[PDB]
Image (cartoon, rainbow over all chains, first blue to last red; front, side, top):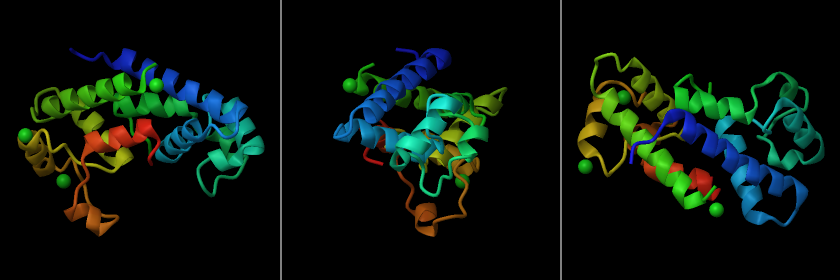
Length: 93
Length: 89
Ligand SMILES: [Cl-]
Ligand SMILES: [Cl-]
Ligand SMILES: [Cl-]
């Protein structure tokens, strides 16, 4: 089966959103938090939007990339944007 | 979204880009996608696609530099995609 770039990007974001929501709402969600932490470290982001990345960095900072200050989350791309960069070949860096 | 299904689809997407990248004909986007996957996930090709992997490696789509062990001991992109969705890191 052929894979469409836009559709796969949408599914990944959706998967990540499910994970983020579980990691934040509920502690002890060990695997959601692991998935979220892996996405955040790999893509260098901390949220589905600028606003959720800021919120996560203030309230659940352990989920954010190491050495991440709060205020960078205001200016850095969010995880949805980094997922788009990945599949379009823009570059995560 | 099912974890197994999405990891499968992303690997298939990566495989598609890999085979397109080997053709140097209006595939500059596929080359960028392959290179982006390689740098983001820290991998180079897949053990399941040895012929393609050898070609992109020669096309300098697995650039070296940081982590010298990772320059000689390349990681499988399929495994790294699996690690991404399993949260293994
Ligand atoms: Cl699942
Ligand atoms: Cl092979
Ligand atoms: Cl190379």
